[PDB]
Image (cartoon, coloured by chain):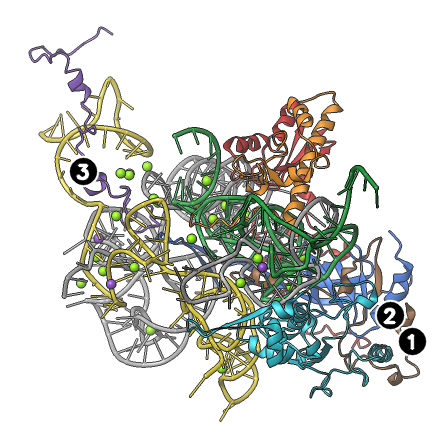
Chain colours: A blue, B red, C purple, D brown, E cyan, F orange, G yellow, H green
Amino acid sequence: QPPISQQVKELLPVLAAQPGHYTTIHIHGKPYLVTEGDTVKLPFKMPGVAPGDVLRLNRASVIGSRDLTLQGAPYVDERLFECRAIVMGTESEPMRVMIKKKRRCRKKKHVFSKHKYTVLRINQLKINDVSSL
Amino acid sequence: SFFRITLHRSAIGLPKRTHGVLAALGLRRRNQTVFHPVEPQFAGMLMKVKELVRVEEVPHRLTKRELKDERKPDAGFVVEKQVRRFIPGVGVQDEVDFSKVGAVVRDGKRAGDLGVRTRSDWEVIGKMKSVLPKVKAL
Amino acid sequence: IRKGRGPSSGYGKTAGRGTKGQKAHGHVKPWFQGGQTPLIVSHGRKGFVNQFAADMSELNLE
Amino acid sequence: QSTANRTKRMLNIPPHESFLNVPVEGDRIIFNPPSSEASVYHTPFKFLPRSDPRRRANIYKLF
Amino acid sequence: MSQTVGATRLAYSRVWHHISAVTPHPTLSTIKAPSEAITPPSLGRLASRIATILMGKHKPIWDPSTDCGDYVVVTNCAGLYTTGHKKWRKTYYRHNTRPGSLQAITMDALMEKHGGAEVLRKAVSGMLPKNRLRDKRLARLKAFEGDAHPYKENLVRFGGKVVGAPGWEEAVKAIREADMERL
Amino acid sequence: GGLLWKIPWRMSKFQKLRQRRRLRAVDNVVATIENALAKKGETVKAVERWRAEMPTEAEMLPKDKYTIFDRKEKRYRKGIHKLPKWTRVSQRVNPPGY
RNA sequence: AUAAGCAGCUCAAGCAAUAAGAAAGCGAGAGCGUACCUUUUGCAUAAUGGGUCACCAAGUUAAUUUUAGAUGCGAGCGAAU
RNA sequence: GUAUGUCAAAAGGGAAACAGCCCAGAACAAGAGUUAAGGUUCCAAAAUUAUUAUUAAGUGAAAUAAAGAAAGUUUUUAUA
RNA sequence: CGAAAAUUUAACGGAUCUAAAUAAUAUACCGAAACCUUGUCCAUAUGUAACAUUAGUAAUAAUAUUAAUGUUAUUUGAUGGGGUAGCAGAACGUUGAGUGAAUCUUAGAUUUUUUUUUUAUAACUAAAUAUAGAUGAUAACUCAAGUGAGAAUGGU
Ligand SMILES: [K+]
Ligand SMILES: [K+]
Ligand SMILES: [K+]
Ligand SMILES: [Mg+2]
Ligand SMILES: [Mg+2]
Ligand SMILES: [Mg+2]
Ligand SMILES: [Mg+2]
Ligand SMILES: [Mg+2]
Ligand SMILES: [Mg+2]
Ligand SMILES: [Mg+2]
Ligand SMILES: [Mg+2]
Ligand SMILES: [Mg+2]
Ligand SMILES: [Mg+2]
Ligand SMILES: [Mg+2]
Ligand SMILES: [Mg+2]
Ligand SMILES: [Mg+2]
Ligand SMILES: [Mg+2]
Ligand SMILES: [Mg+2]
Ligand SMILES: [Mg+2]
Ligand SMILES: [Mg+2]
Ligand SMILES: [Mg+2]
Ligand SMILES: [Mg+2]
Ligand SMILES: [Mg+2]
Ligand SMILES: [Mg+2]
Ligand SMILES: [Mg+2]
Ligand SMILES: [Mg+2]
């Protein structure tokens, strides 16, 4: 695999040594700035997942600390970090009624929408030691 | 060679003939791509809608699948551990952990065949009043 | 089809009659063609119906 | 506005200029000191034990 | 959501900014060369920068509903810069709904009654959203004719050096060098 | 007339830029079709007629890009943006002399 | 009680449960939106109609003549003994 | 009358407001997503972004008032 | 400069602008319910699997299969999606009747309300109040209509 840069191999230990860390995961291309312990509520029902399934997130746009920020050109190398989530369940919104109507026309067409949403829980967000790599 | 034709503009207020040059090409909606061989019959069909489409020379024709896959976004996640499930058509799929790789689906007419802990199993587990953890481990 | 029972039924306000015509207010005679003379008058009725002809029950050898 | 999507575009604030310089040719780590108050968990080097190896020159000096 | 979890006290606090209508502004001036021709910010160009501060639109936490604006103390409004013949040919109008009661006045005549501070308030006023926060935001514009004002102790400072002073920048960089001596 | 169709007599520097890029995009569509056919030693009558009596954006004068011919005007010139569907219609050549 | 909203919708501070748990409602502030029907080429129209609410209030029945679908019998069908 | 389109029966963005014009055809959501017409100092999302010239009249800047006058000014082409 | 009209600056939308004007160019960005992406709803298809029901055909003393209908999932990673006059299809609700000499009800049937959930013109959960054993209510399927009202200067 492509070797990690020498500049990233010397500053990553300083990035992981700081108190807090955040990441910008990309689910189906859409970003989500999360932290270890956050609860992500995706705007769609992930198909083929039941409450309790563990997912490994491998597309991170930015993984930075207070002062330092690791940025990959398209994305960061998966070997640097390890982010995992757990499927907590599915939530739904209240029914919304949209009334499509025109002036001087009695017909009022109704549109009932009630979408489901998958809820995740970031239970692991750690930076790996790349001293050997 | 093929012509990669993409409808960049619409033809709402354009004459009906323009609409049926686009129908012959297969451009129904906006930003729709179609592939046609490089021939006079198709080249003249584009000169009528040259103000609406974007043409490009491509070596081969792309299948409908590949064209969709160009815009597909990376999933960004991998299901590594699946809890026990019940497939309505197959049966009960036991817990599987892909981190150490086994999706075994047991179907039957009795609780034992499903592979779950039954009431009888709980009774034999409660009768083993002699099993004890090793003192070193305790 | 119950006409005049709302707009979403498709047969509501006007019940499929149009807008304020003779076909909406009243009734048009069935034989009326707007005033133009019918062909039965322009051409006339041809022939006569034989009221004395016998009516046979046709039977075939087949 | 009429919908929530439009309200979001009007109330938009772009990200900090440091993140806009997305890298190319690979990954890199940039020094991005935020303009905010540090928490009590960023212990100053003066309060670190002599045994703590994390003591080190300012990360600014590493660049 | 983590980005917004913390102490938002200082993000909403009112900062007292200062600017002189006579000091050349390399950014808000139309002339950029030679440096000796760099003029101060014109009436409207200064009012466009002030209206942005009164709205708080310069903050990363801006919201039009929340009044997250700041103060702007403008001095030397007597030497307010204008181009062309705006000073003597521009007119301000007024009507109180009574036919015949149309009041007109030029800029030079308005600067004699209420000074250049009123000319800058009408400019900033028209650049603010026409809503119920327009009078509060405009009231935070402290315009004065000369160099004196009662807010010489309110102006934001960094190490005792008021922003815009000769050595305020080096006083800021010196305080951030010490903030890096921590984990 | 009392119905107001507020249409300025001249275009802005933004409409002119997009107009230049539209005239330039139609030149690439014909150049792509003309070159793709030349490789096969083939030609279409329409392409020949276009390349013969229609100029490219780099060969047009500014007055041919932003104005059209209108005999009802005192100078026989009219803003090109006053033409129906001017954005998606091809107009480049005016009568000679005007 | 500094304000020019067909009174809804989008964003939303705050108040609101004496208590473990549990936030319906009201909403400052910002933005979007000129009732409905009828009738017209076209209506926020200063064109028609209605003070509000509840109730009564309009393609139905018969005979006749047809069509589609389903179904019974079938060169016969139906009715009646 | 003819040719073409829109409205009528088409919402949405642009033209300050807008049946008919410029774009574009609304099944419902999410996104600093990609674009059209149109725009990017502030009201108000986006450049006080670059280059070369003209104007000094706020002319003008999203609805061109005319012939005409004139040591206004710039440029070119002749010329002393 | 020519250039004068009657409520008020009065066709830059306004503030304002010496460019934030004009002309000839270049690039980035913004920008619609358009497009893409990830999900959902609906319509119409195409094959396959499984679940239930109904009616058949076989097996069984030491369960399989056929067809129709409903339904979920899935294959082609299927296609389609504004609308007046108007045409067409599929449903809900209301009133009465059949099954019904049925079913349920002080261990709370019914209670014009409130609340909760479910793709929902509907039903359901629970709460509060009152107290009925049938002149009470009721699923499902079917039958028949005095069957659905913000609009008639409508009527009471
Ligand atoms: K009335
Ligand atoms: K009725
Ligand atoms: K002007
Ligand atoms: Mg049409
Ligand atoms: Mg209809
Ligand atoms: Mg009809
Ligand atoms: Mg009919
Ligand atoms: Mg009528
Ligand atoms: Mg008629
Ligand atoms: Mg008018
Ligand atoms: Mg008040
Ligand atoms: Mg009226
Ligand atoms: Mg009654
Ligand atoms: Mg009734
Ligand atoms: Mg039919
Ligand atoms: Mg009509
Ligand atoms: Mg429209
Ligand atoms: Mg504008
Ligand atoms: Mg963006
Ligand atoms: Mg802005
Ligand atoms: Mg004005
Ligand atoms: Mg769409
Ligand atoms: Mg559509
Ligand atoms: Mg439809
Ligand atoms: Mg009750
Ligand atoms: Mg009435």
- Label 3 residue SS: loop
- Amino acid carrying label 2: it is Val
Q: Residues within 10 Å of mark 2 (few under 14, many from 20)?
A: some
Looking at the rendered structure, whether the residues under marks 1 and 2 are on a common chain is answered as: no
Q: Nearer the viewer, mark 2 or mark 3?
A: 3
Quadrant location, ligand no. 15: top left
Corner quadrant of residue C1: top left
Q: CA distance from mark 1 to mark 2?
A: 10 Å
Tell me whether marks 2 and 3 sit on the same chain: no
Circle 1 chain: D
For the residues carrying marks 1 and 3, which lies nearer the camera in this image?
3
Binning the other alpha carbons within 10 Å of mark 3 as few (below 14), some (14 to 19) or many (20 upward) gives: few
The 10 Å Cα crowd at callout 1, few under 14, some 14 to 19, many 20 or more, is some
Which amino acid type is shown beneath numbered disc 1?
Answer: Arg
Cα separation between marks 1 and 3:
101 Å
Please provide percent x and percent y for residue A50. 62, 59
The quadrant holding residue E26 is bottom right
Do labels 2 and 3 touch, CB within 8 Å? no
Please give the residue where the numbered disc 2 appears in the rendered image: A14
Residue A51 % position (x, y): 62, 62
| Label 1 close to label 2 by CB (< 8 Å) | yes
* Residue pointed to by mark 3: C27
Distance between the Cα atoms at labels 2 and 3?
Answer: 93 Å
Q: Amino acid at mark 3?
A: His
Q: Which mark is residue D56?
A: 1
